[PDB]
Length: 21
Length: 30
Image (cartoon, each protein chain N blue to C red):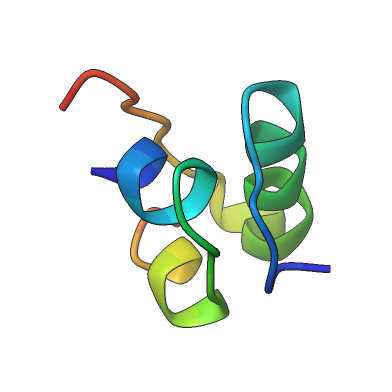
């Protein structure tokens, strides 16, 4: 989930954009 | 600014800036 991918590990734009509506 | 560890209010801020008028969903448990 977003915390494992972007907080516990280095985030990316690809992954952040998956959470945009 | 996105390619780093982003936690708590810093993650929500990055979602806010990247997603713009789309908005976003922040689901930290799931």
